[PDB]
Image 1 (spheres, each protein chain N blue to C red):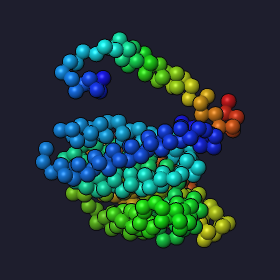
Image 2: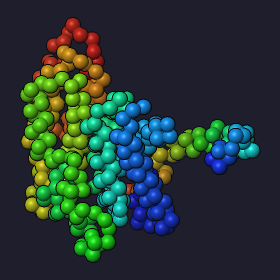
Image 3: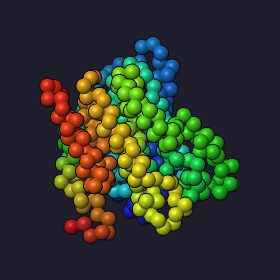
Image 4: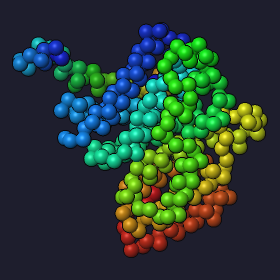
Length: 292
Length: 48
């Protein structure tokens, strides 16, 4: 895809084509989660769910991965694209947090899709109290007459009520880290929350004030190297507490999800903060389960 | 074929067309774009 060129110059039929491509995918996975909630007991809707997990999730994940790796989306974002993206985010986050026999089969798939989506999306969503600073936000775009025109709750917290905020999520993950809760009891957190924080902090590093003493407090969001330090320390210390038990390929993949963060982090911290990592990974000489 | 799928007859009048598509055209797209990642991804930054 080259949506930059397509959007700057291209035909409105093509515009509406990809707009319908994303709208239809949205309504598809929303109707999928709905019929899954009404699917308390175990066929057409089941086929829709299977089609979702096999095709709709991979394509959205891949196109958002390309968007993220091109540092893309700021011009891609247009009318109703915000609304579709927020709906999709709430949907797959709801499935990831929810527990069902359907969820435990492809919960990894939604995990990678949400990891791609959170980075790909061009507006800071996990922070909402000072998010007004972004002119690219649809709230700044819509003035008031367009707000009255389109059916949206006019409050960012109301549009995504189920999702929590960054500070409460980081304090909760620190709490579960120090408590050392096993992955089996609450797979959803260690399955979806970590890709959230990873992608979010990876792409709003530079849309944080630490790179940018300039335009300070005109930032779309506020972030710190100490936030990065805290949460990758949490990742290393949770893996510390839980390679001994329950093992699993999920810790094998959170390594590659945390790879951007370990490239991001500065090297003086690397020295004497991942020296613990190398010794903790090898202290289980008796075990054979793969790590990193 | 979706319209005729509601019919009992599963025989497809354009079976040659659909097999040619699935066996050649769809993989032809695959090989062409995987060989030409960069060419369509030109972004005025003079890539190659």
